[PDB]
Amino acid sequence: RKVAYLTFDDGPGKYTAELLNTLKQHDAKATFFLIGANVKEFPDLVKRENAEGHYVGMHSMTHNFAKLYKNGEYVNEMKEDQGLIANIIGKSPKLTRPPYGSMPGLNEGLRNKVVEGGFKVWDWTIDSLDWRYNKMPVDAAAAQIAQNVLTNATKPQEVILMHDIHPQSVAAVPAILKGLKEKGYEFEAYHEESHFPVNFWHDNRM
Amino acid sequence: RKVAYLTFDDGPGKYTAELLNTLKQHDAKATFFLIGANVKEFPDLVKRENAEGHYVGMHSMTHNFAKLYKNGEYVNEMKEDQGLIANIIGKSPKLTRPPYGSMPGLNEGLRNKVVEGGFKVWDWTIDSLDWRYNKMPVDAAAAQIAQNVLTNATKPQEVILMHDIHPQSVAAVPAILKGLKEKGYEFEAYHEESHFPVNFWHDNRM
Amino acid sequence: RKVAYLTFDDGPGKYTAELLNTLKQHDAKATFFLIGANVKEFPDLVKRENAEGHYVGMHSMTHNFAKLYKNGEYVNEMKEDQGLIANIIGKSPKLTRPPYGSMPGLNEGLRNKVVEGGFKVWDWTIDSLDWRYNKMPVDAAAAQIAQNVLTNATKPQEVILMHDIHPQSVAAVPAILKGLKEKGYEFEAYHEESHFPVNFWHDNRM
Amino acid sequence: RKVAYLTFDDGPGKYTAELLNTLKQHDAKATFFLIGANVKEFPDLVKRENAEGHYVGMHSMTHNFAKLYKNGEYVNEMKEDQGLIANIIGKSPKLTRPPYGSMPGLNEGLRNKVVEGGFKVWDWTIDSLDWRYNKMPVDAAAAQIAQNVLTNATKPQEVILMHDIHPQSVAAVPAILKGLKEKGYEFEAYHEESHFPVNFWHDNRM
Ligand SMILES: NCCCC[C@H](N)C(=O)NO
Ligand SMILES: NCCCC[C@H](N)C(=O)NO
Ligand SMILES: NCCCC[C@H](N)C(=O)NO
Ligand SMILES: NCCCC[C@H](N)C(=O)NO
Ligand SMILES: [Zn+2]
Ligand SMILES: [Zn+2]
Ligand SMILES: [Zn+2]
Ligand SMILES: [Zn+2]
């Protein structure tokens, strides 16, 4: 069967509640990788995301490339983010989504620490390219983003990269949600017990 | 709708003519990001690149991370470079390719200065890793470099990072051209009028 | 009669146990040259290497070129490393593998002292270059590293240089083990009584 | 048809005349790559080799790995050696044979200088392994060396690596001369107008 994993990064943000409504209204479950600072200021949205059956994973504290990878703080930031999230939803998530992807940032050393810290790493198989259409008219932008993901949806499993801190991104989702549904896809959240590898390194320990 | 953008960096140099010839035989256009000192040493090579339908953009004067980013010479160096190139081909190009990529060197300040200067910044979506294959037979280095490229071309647009200043890179170009062409790609040069953002910062102003 | 001597340097490490299993699974014997710091921290892995029919040789304490060769600490470091290994496996190995190879580091003075100390020296006849392949997907890297080795196996004896301290390296070994066996090689460990010279200096006293 | 290019390195030496006799009486042509100091001390042998129709190439001045490749003195030494030989045989030879082979020593920069200085570079396709049997009974040693090349001779063109500064090598030559002669090989010397590439880098400019 075809399963589609919508993933949303850099949240929560001010369009997240509209997204959570749009998703719920189509009974569609998704995954959110949250930044620590946005977890601090939107505890409600965090609690709601988990409450409406979506997976709530980490996307670090600083979203800073040099700190995470060059200064080796990745796993440390993923753990601190994990704590903040656990304080709200009462579970300690294991799935991380690397800021800027894992390639080339997540070197062999840091990949051991992730494995040793108990974390998984997910990248994506489709880039919605939503960041291109920023600060542009929302509906035109969103329609293009929609077509971006739909025409690249070909494989039995797909992990789609989006950003709910962008209006054109959240606006893109309704057209994506059932356009993908007719191609036979279903919209699941990530489940830890059903982990399968999706990382640029093809590193199957994560 | 598929378009491959071969880009070659740190040229011109002693293999560039052989590469320019390979490009010509295949009627393939591409893009060159030049270092200022090589602009001055091989001024006729520059002419010919632009004369055969390739884009000529800048890749700095010093290629020195500390000077470019920590000290913020970037926009200066790309301007100086631009001037040299203009004096030879007439055009003042706008596109720049950052040494060592934009991430994390081009901070928001420099990025502001870039867009303020009218300049533009390209990174890449495929890294051929061509320059690292320098301690094996050239023909075998070229085959692994071609394979790297051919097996990552998937998106409707691909910006392929290469260097025309290593023999194994230029030797890879024939295999790469034939392979991608099998995959339905066209080999156009960058066009100024037809710009779309391609950078690690996801900053669509540049 | 064709024999392939897989040698693994700078271990033991965190992929070593998995390497030991893959070896064991193909009924294959190999050689390990160990650094002093890792013999101390992975003593079990050392005993297992020996216990499972592999040769356990030295690869110094510091892996530092200036201390080993410029300051002449080579024989000292190999002796200290020898002591550490013997406290674990109960025999004092004589074969050493020079960090960075013997050329040009092991000058005649040090080569004389090596000879006067009872030590043997092995360089290699095939460089897998496996450690250089740390910036691509691990399976892709392993396949190219396999290719490197398979295409250079031409002589009845081949001493292949690898590193069991990198993920892409241990992943390459299955394809190497299957290609070379198909090319007719057998995978033996170094035996001290059967010593034959393999060094860049063509010095057959080592 | 089959042609065998016997090449002898590091000479001339004290068995060179005995080899030149062994060659002449078997109506056999060869190639000698000479060290500058041995050219200085054996002008007769140098003159004789050319006078008797063999090719006389360079093998550098110091035979020092670090000087040649790391300090980039390779081409300088081949030119200084070229001068010495030209003063004897009245022509300036173009073919050089890299001490310790060209891999990895002859990097891309140096391969350009060799190309720009007008030099060619030959490695070999067969290593006689003659250095292993040094200071050993000449008779046994020579027989093994003879077969070493014989068991590795399969291709229409073969460049055998030998050393006429060793007794066991020169003694091996008679037996080699008859194994190859039976396989249909002919023993021609290298001649410059018929140059074809034989180098570990597969750099076909050399
Ligand atoms: N607005 C996008 C900035 C960062 C994009 C990058 N792909 C990432 O870290 N997504 O979570
Ligand atoms: N190993 C240093 C990186 C150099 C390559 C870099 N990607 C670049 O600027 N190419 O043009
Ligand atoms: N310059 C890289 C050093 C690694 C290769 C070297 N031959 C070695 O020490 N192996 O153990
Ligand atoms: N007696 C062997 C010393 C040098 C061997 C090496 N293969 C070489 O440079 N031959 O010319
Ligand atoms: Zn992000
Ligand atoms: Zn560059
Ligand atoms: Zn080592
Ligand atoms: Zn030599």
Image: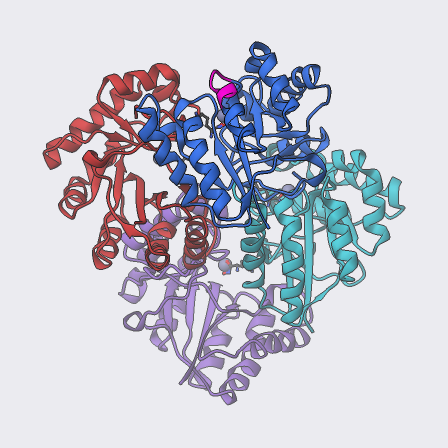
Chain colours: A purple, B cyan, C red, D blue
How far from the left and from the top, in percent, is residue C75? Answer: 27, 20
Is A152 or B23 nearer to us in this picture?
A: B23
Instruction: State the residue lying farthest toward the bottom.
Output: A182
Instruction: State the residue lying farthest toward the front.
Output: D25
Is A76 or D160 nearer to us in this picture?
A: D160
Query: Can residue C21 be seen from the camera position used here?
Result: yes
- What residue is shown at x 33% (from left), y 56% (from top)? C184
How far from the left and from the top, in percent, is residue D25? Answer: 54, 29
When asked about the image quadrant of residue D198, the answer is top right
Quarter of the figure with the C terminus of chain D:
top right
State ligand 6's quadrant: top right
The residue segment tinted magenta is: D13-18
Vertical relation: D89 (above or below) C175: above
- What residue is shown at x 62% (from left), y 37% (from top)? B69
- What residue is shown at x 65% (from left), y 75% (from top)? A144
Is D82 or B197 nearer to us in this picture?
A: D82
The reply, left or right, for residue C136 in relation to residue C13 is: right
Vertical relation: A202 (above or below) A128: above
When asked about the image quadrant of residue B15, the answer is top right
